[PDB]
Length: 544
Figure 1 (cartoon, one colour):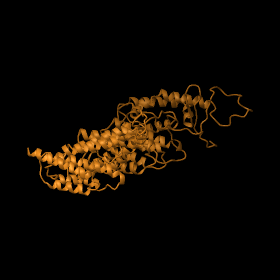
Figure 2 (cartoon, rainbow, N blue to C red):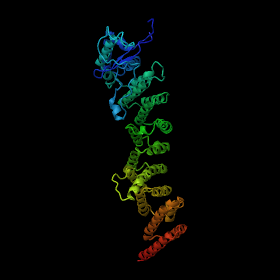
Figure 3 (tube, rainbow, N blue to C red):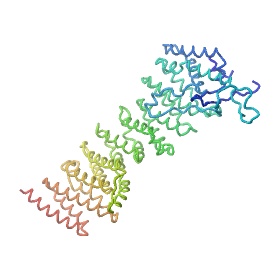
Figure 4 (cartoon, one colour):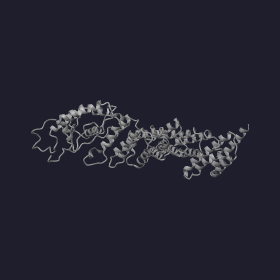
């Protein structure tokens, strides 16, 4: 009897299509629809609605409800939604907890703006103007009364703001009432209603988290509704945020997360574009994913996936997000230090190398830097990529520290760390290169154990470190600085580890062989003679 929900049961079939008038006096919008006008001309319907929602509000029994009653409540709520009466923003707290903002309002049909609020009668006739059908001001009066009656009712608090009506039946019927077809009749509120239903059902699930089966069902429904076609981009974005939230709330849904990562994040494209991950919302999405890296259940899968790390490499190439990725990585390494599993090393080291390779923009600034310094002039705003340069330095420091706190390496990761430090040592940036050589020297002299069963021969250390780098010196003029740094590090490491006694003169023999490989140009030869004098000095010193 609420004259809003009905069933399929004059000479013109015209159902009076929906039109909206927004006026100009203040900011007040009035929808005019067939359901709206029928509600405006039915006092009995107004009484029925107010009493029905009062009864729903007071009813302190979840079990005494029926399935048909739940369906009727949902249908009334949805009908008020589609008539532009019920405010779509039902749960502002959930939107603020995430970083979404003001669910897409169900758009009206063909709309007419009424600048003047007054009566009609003999006016605006025989002088062009007009033309639209438009409400006859009685429909306008009725629609105003309809909005007033609905606001006098407290639908939002009556149904959801009860804390006892929110049981599995409500979420189930809300999901089952969703629409999966874009009919021409309901084209104006398809995506909006999808988002509204998803958000409201997720909020109601938040109110009752200790229902595992309901969680699985709601996740399945959300995924099925998301994989549909003909959805605008913003709908896909919001549903992505909702999907990651639901995955976080549940306990063991590894397959769904795999589907999310692979299908949505890696393959979509042109949707998860550059700007999407910098909109205050992509940051929330990424923070949710990284927090999901720390959980009782979603740990082992998120470690050994290689598609998670492929996506991490994709998002760490983005200029703005690099600092956030580095902060997450650094916190994970410092706090528990268990993110580095037995097989995770190459991926995380790749992420570190990517965040340390900002020497591109470093030398981009350095171009004009050297252009103005080679002249007798002055530059004040220095290192426009100062954030990027400091990030690269912190990444190299993170690698240096990463060579520690494990103590059970396989020497493959040792070679990898040394190679990564060298590869950054090739970098154009002067500060980056200097930090790389300094930290590589420090790590080599006081961070790798010499007489360990893992690696008990410094020859292999040198030959998996500097030797592989110098074997690829085919960069023409760029080889001179790289070789000078390589040999300088070699000499320093050789001296430092000789000063601590030790044995295996094959170390000396191999270093001599490397020097012979670079014996040309005689500058390396004089360096060899100098370190030979240093060798004699160390001989005397260790003797006495």
